[PDB]
Structures are given as structure tokens and as C-alpha cells.
Length: 271
Image (cartoon, rainbow, N blue to C red; front, side):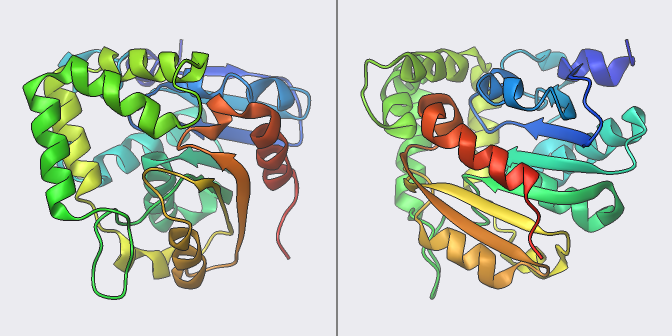
């Protein structure tokens, strides 16, 4: 064991390849299992680090410090502690949903630790603003948080199909509904509020490591224009690939389409 960082985040390292280190970081409502279809494609060429974000279902709620995680910085500090403990000189970081922004934030502090960021289903701001389309108004958020607080289980059951998209009887929808409901309900409401009310747009000019912006063409939480926004405001080189998939966790729900795209963005560098 690497110690508390491993135990607290259920951290695992798999693969024996020599081309680099990859760190995979999941979105709200899921856990490292979201990467189950990607990892087999990476173990020949890479060492792959998987971990659960603090507050995720599989983590000990006693380690959830509300003051630490009241901003997204807390999660970025956790990521930097993982990379420091692993003695990583450099990694390829793939961040899903909120973990995309968490990696971007961490890369501002320590750009040396990241050769590239793959930003999957990423958004710097969910709320609409003047000349900015995120996909949500405050009233939408308020209605969502009221549903979460009124019956969390029912909310999970209704939200998962919308978020995952596609056929509501799919194994992916069922998996996500269960991982959503694994989060302790106080942590879930708090975290959803923190993430959905976030706005990191003014930090994007500080991100200088190359970014690969990948998303579904139809995503509940991420209008396609957000990818263009990211591409036009990140402070370093970037590329955008909008996939012919639907859903916010497309690496889980449509891996036949999505895993080839993620593998390409991991293997090929922008000029």
C-alpha cells in the first residue's frame, strides 16, 4: 500500500507498459469503474492510475471535509497529493466531467506534472451567462436540488437515464443509477451544488498544457458549444472532437464508439 492516499481514494495502478503514465479521474455520480472499457486498451503501453474522487460512493464519508471541498480546489489538491505520492514526473491525465476541470486546475499549479489533459464531457460553467451558453438556468438547478433533497433515491432513478442517455433499460443506465445512489445523500447534494454552481472560465487562460476536448454530440449537461468555448479560451494548444455518441458518460454507455476516440487522443499529440 502507498498509505492513506491509496486507502482514501481506493487507488489502483495497473499495466506494465513503458510509453507513459496515465491517470484516469471520474465524474460526479460514478467511480473508477466508469473506466472499465478503456483500461484494457492502455495496459500494453502504459501504467494506469485509477482512483475515486473523495465523496464518491466507494469512499469513506468520514474523510469528506465540507470545508475542503467547498470549492473545486480541494479536489485539485487531492489530485496533486496523489501525483506527489506516486512520484510521477509527468502523466497523461484523462478527466471525466468535473474531473476535467479538476485536472485543469491542478495543471495551473503544476504544469510540469501533465504532458496532456484529455477533457471528456467537460464544462467550465453550467449556468448560462451573457454571451455564454452552459445549458442551465438557476431555476433548473434549484428544481434539481429540491428533487435531490426531497427523495434522493427517486431523483437518482429519474436523473440517471437522462444523464446517460440512450435506452433507459441499458446496463449503463442501471449502473449509473446505482453509483449515484451510493453517494451519501448529504455529500451528493453538497457536491452537486458545488459543481453545478461552479464557474472556472476566468482560470482557463492559465491552463497551458495541451488539451484534447472530447464530448458527445448530445450531452444533458454539456451543449456542444461548450467545447468550442473551451477551445477558444484555454491558454495553450487544444483540439476538439465531438463524437457521434449521446450521453454524459459515453465511455461507459457507448464504448464501441468512444474508446477508439479516447485511445487516439491519448496516443496522438497536437503539434
